[PDB]
Amino acid sequence: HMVKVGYIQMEPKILELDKNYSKAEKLIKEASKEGAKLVVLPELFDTGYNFESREEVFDVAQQIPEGETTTFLMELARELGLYIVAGTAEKSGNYLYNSAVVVGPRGYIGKYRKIHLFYREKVFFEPGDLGFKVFDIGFAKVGVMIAFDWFFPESARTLALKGAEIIAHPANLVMPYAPRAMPIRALENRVYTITADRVGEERGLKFIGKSLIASPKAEVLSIASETEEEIGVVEIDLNLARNKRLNDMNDIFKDRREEYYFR
Amino acid sequence: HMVKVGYIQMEPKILELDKNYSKAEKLIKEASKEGAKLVVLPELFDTGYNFESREEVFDVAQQIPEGETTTFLMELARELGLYIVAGTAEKSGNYLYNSAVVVGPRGYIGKYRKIHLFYREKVFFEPGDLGFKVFDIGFAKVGVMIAFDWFFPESARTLALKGAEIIAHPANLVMPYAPRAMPIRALENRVYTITADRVGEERGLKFIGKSLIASPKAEVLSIASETEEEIGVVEIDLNLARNKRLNDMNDIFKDRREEYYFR
Ligand SMILES: [Cl-]
Ligand SMILES: [Cl-]
Image (cartoon, rainbow over all chains, first blue to last red; front, side):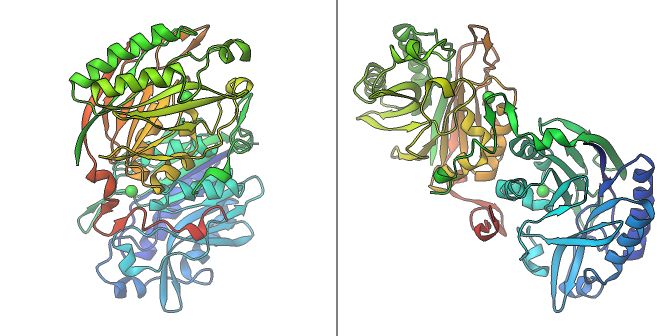
């Protein structure tokens, strides 16, 4: 029930897939040496974010799972004996999705397509259509959401109600709020959250860094710099997430009264 | 559009209804002079909180709206021409509810019964059975929730989806979290929140104070001390709560995708 998990805070270079693979590899190898068994990369780590046209992203985006990003991550996950959740631009026929892939030693585990698109993403990407999924990685059940999904408390709630013990959260954050909000998402659901943000400025848009890992008690177990590429790895206690008792008398999920919600 | 609202942070003395009325009156008179048109009093401001048995509270609890607490609040609201949301122990036949009463210049408006009971409340009180209600007070729609209701993101979400522009939140807080959480509840629903907490130690139980008013942008507009009785009144812009645009391409409520939540 104790396991080491981490974020990889990196600076994707827009449209330079090979360079971004190399950077991810370097940092993930560092995280593996610290003992991480699950690592999370940022939203759109492979392509970058701040596109000018649909064409330029459509021309580089890879299919999941046959394409280059997924195959790269598979090789790395098997080499290092760990699980990776990573944000990537997904080409599916004529459509692009803002996706996250989950890989492990056995290969491709599954994917998530961003349900709540943010700002100009609606110009490039189709809204996600697979719902909120929880993946079994043996030592834990891991839910995935991407960036702006944090804003909707229903995102994490749905993952937690489906049995997520850890929420892996690839992100490219631009608003100042997520670092204050994510510990509340962790607290209200009694889960661990791993927000992996990028850094840098990209065609005029500044990302905020501040990747963080939050506990079921709203503790910030690790928080990154605003500007620097870095990893954060911490040991988490999965029993703290499986036990929904806030105190002796209140189990948070048994205390929900659905008949009074949304009505 | 622009209106002044406030919290009253007081220290109820357990079982001393008349003393608590006098204290509330004093502080609400101060809030009226500052221009408040809506004031929120703490959870169970009339009875206090940390009961030793159900009998002790059953013996002082008042009916709503015929009982002493509601009639007191009605007299005060008429005299000062304002709206009051206040936490009170409700006697309803043979049952006790941990309730909030809404009154205005013309009299009794309605009530709310705490849906999510916290810790030893379960020993004294029946779980609320009226659902989450929004009350029309002319210049605004006010939703009400009580104390531990904050922990469940569905509480504020249900109020906001029913049209709440302000969430009045009587509370007796003992955990450290709500002052960090309330701005996120405001932000995610684009509403104002007024958390009126008590202070003091009562039979060994310490309340945290820190009453606060939060904006749709997660700004703490006013926050009280840990220990002192005080008021806080601020001018809020109700158009910032009515307009759910986060930015020029994302409207928070139009961006919700219910088909993917809880399933
Ligand atoms: Cl953001
Ligand atoms: Cl609390």
